[PDB]
Length: 104
Length: 56
Image (cartoon, rainbow over all chains, first blue to last red; front, side):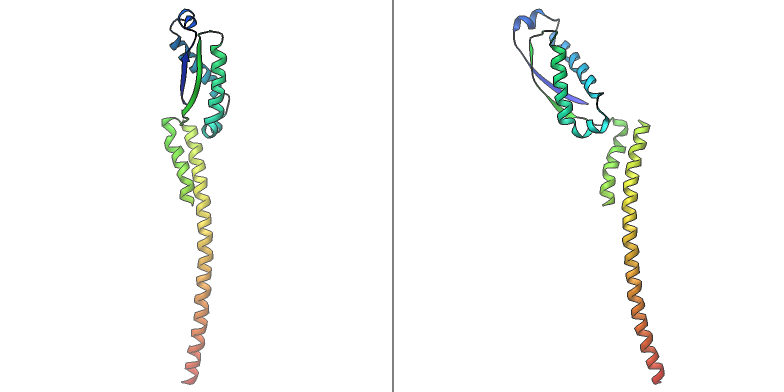
């Protein structure tokens, strides 16, 4: 699973005097929230409709997680890159994709 | 990883088998039609041969 998160800085007092290195803290919070959201849904739902639900839920979880820290960072948008299966089983997946074309 | 790869191979094999079944059915009905046409032509040819043999 790959995602990109874009954020901006508001209230510089909080950005400078709340958390040590807020960028790394936001990175770890994003990773934890993405871990929490991906494990809720099954594999095929992630593979097919991953562009909207997973990306949308991730945003809600990230806001909820970084709210207590009060970093002052405002979360603009999180978007989607890829929900590719692992490299070891890619051949099985694309072969299964090509199977329907072979049948036709 | 092995388990998921096996499942995906299962799905692919099922799809290919369904396609092969459809192709086999179509080829079978085609062969039946070909045989029927050839049999009709052979019957007409036999009638002509019998006519010639009787005339001779």
